[PDB]
Image 1: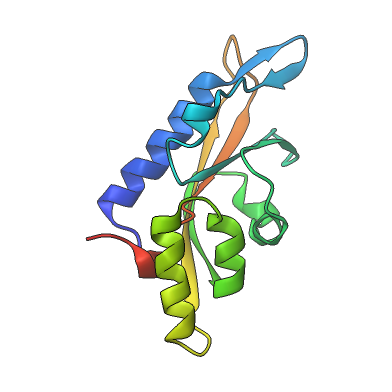
Image 2 (image 1 turned 180 degrees about the vertical axis):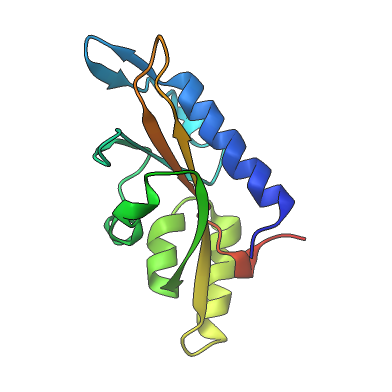
Length: 146
């Protein structure tokens, strides 16, 4: 389930990467230093107006397969369910949550995890072509803080 905090985090990251991105010589450039890459747990994906991926913050095949093409045309919100192993492949970043994730695995037979997804479509501007930015919250809602 979405909460206001998640809405702001996802939208904020979307704006961060839209602002960071630049189009030059017919190509998208996302010059991303490491400390900003690790700043947030979220994972950002950027597609062109035809739904083709231009840049991914991290490459996680199972998740990419779950982002439906028809979700990339207009602003929206979506939730994707996945098993614990897939979530571990998506988080695979900072122990804190990871430690909690293993706790969930042990104490549940086949717990289902749910990941929050926000889609933001940016109309073309004088300096950037039309872009669709997808931001995935890598911390499943079952593990969210209160």
